[PDB]
Length: 145
Length: 144
Length: 144
Length: 144
Image 1 (cartoon, helix red, strand yellow):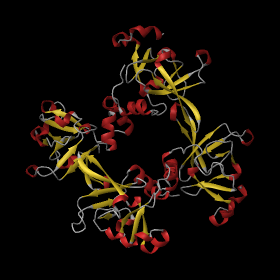
Image 2: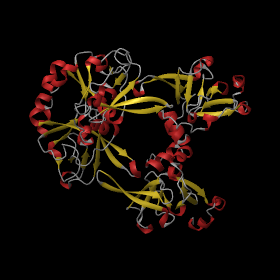
Image 3: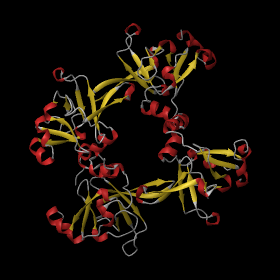
């Protein structure tokens, strides 16, 4: 995979998608349609179409952003330390396109792995289950339920 | 007419269209398709669909940005002093949505009125002549 | 209270005062003279001179920023949800001039209420005890 | 002459002085006191105190920024080309501290050499003639 050039991204991504995925902006809490979307399907990197999260692992955390127990696969995201007042947080980025997705927190539901991935909906595109074969994601349908 | 909220604009405009129209950025020289487009039709504000320029007034100034000799109507655009770089230039913005479009300089051909509007393609949407009726611009077909 | 215009503030505040208070910037760890300051006095809003913190409530655990356990009054600072970074933190702002000051965390000295006001020194002006009378803050010396 | 650390500049320069000198911002036209100041003295870099312009070379250009026919010394400024719409401008920066100062235009008075150094007052500090000895610029009083 080759990430489109920045010049291409400025012309294809909305300003919101660009700020979030390229400049690590955070979308307003509770603002995105995916925040309260719980329909079967997968969420893919808005930039590359890399699968990132399954609807099976999504839950309403009350935090303000699409929230997931885990990424759809171990290698689909990468984690990166950042700091505010020298206090660490873990940023989550997509593997292939290196889009800023969100952050991951150690206080998610224990019986699902203890983690909460709070992800900007702006970084994602939802592929409904019924559309996955056609979109080229058939081999990942099994992760949806 | 009411300009969409900034929130809506961020979710509707590309980064490029947003930076140019909202943040007064300037697209890269020769980068936009409208730089080399010379087909009959009109150029409207990408934000609002307000008519801005006629193809009739577009010419190839060669500088790297779409260039026109005049707005399609005097009131289609507004002029603003831009004191960037210790000089005074006239910024051109759209009337209704107040998008930054570009600048107008007094260095156009005199035989076409002497003004050169250097306008970002990013600020514009081209409506070809053949599509103007369907798009509600039928009354401006005579502006060509 | 009337806050000075943004133009006025650009010419009166230092770069870091402005960025912190007006643009909610965070000064670098250990950058500010107030970090380890323990002289008696008050810290006022650098924009308005509204009292915000007393030296009495300041402490140093080696944090990169001034640290206080409480504001000088309940009403001098306002709390605001800060949803940056897909989490919720509590930003603290000054009441009158609505300066960004920093944030308040629940990890401060247990015996003083549990809070840690982590405050940009750039948001504050220190008024030494000895100058408080002349400066109009005599009534507050008892908080020092 | 001397370029303080970015940290020192953030804490000493006003937001205006900082944005102008460090980030090549342009102050609003007609906004600075020095625009209409014509008193004997020199103008030094606000960052370093490096002498930059003499009041001897200062004139009213009507443009809205302090305007000079020449720098006080050949070596005290450096010049850099930039472009908008592929139109040339020439940025002027101080030699020692590399402060953004303003722009130079080929439209100055002919008898004085034809150049106009259009300089942000924000980038300067005026040292009146009668303060130059005490200020350490005695050697340059001949330039006034």
